[PDB]
Length: 48
Length: 48
Image 1 (tube, each protein chain N blue to C red):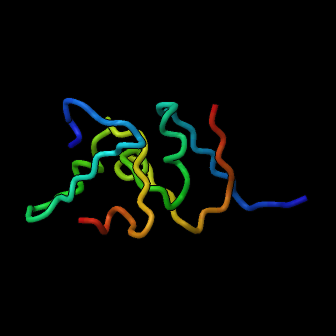
Image 2: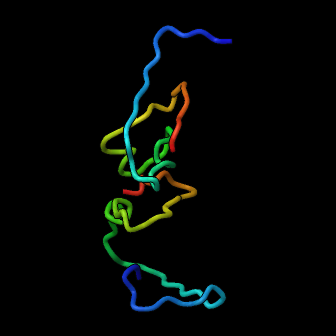
């Protein structure tokens, strides 16, 4: 979903309902390839 | 019109994309591994 081959338009935005997996958000957080990272209900450090 | 006891000028160089990182309470690799401000900060920030 992040290193995807192709993304879609804004009026036809892709939705993926990701379920049943082990999540880790540190690397997604720690990756400097991502320019805009702002969370709105949870402070990101607690997302681990 | 104010007077202070001691002044502490801290100067460095960062990447120009990392300016928003320097605010207290922000969270990000520059603000998380090698320079950290307390939330009760009293002073000014200057970047150019």
